[PDB]
Image 1 (cartoon, one colour):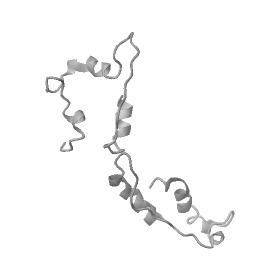
Image 2: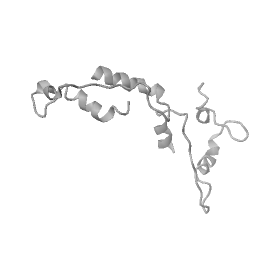
Image 3: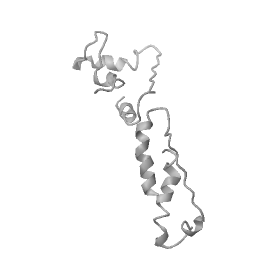
Image 4: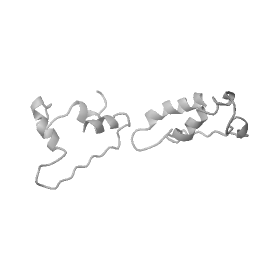
Length: 61
Length: 62
């Protein structure tokens, strides 16, 4: 829990700067898409992060 | 062979942090090999012939 790098995981906050609720699901998905009728791209950088949780993240997404 | 392989296997994790490789490389000099690494011999020459093959595939990674 102390690790800063691992905050987007443990303490994810929105624009309001508050934790998400169960009803914020849809927005989490759009995060990787955009929307239906618009060619779009999503990129994901991983440099400071070890190799033990990489696979976990990948499977989840 | 094993007491070494395992050492490097374990040590890798900490250093290997997403975009680098270990800073502790290790080299092993296998001299006069055909004695204890034959093509076809008895079970006696099996142990030394297995812990070795391991390194021949997944030692570069450590």
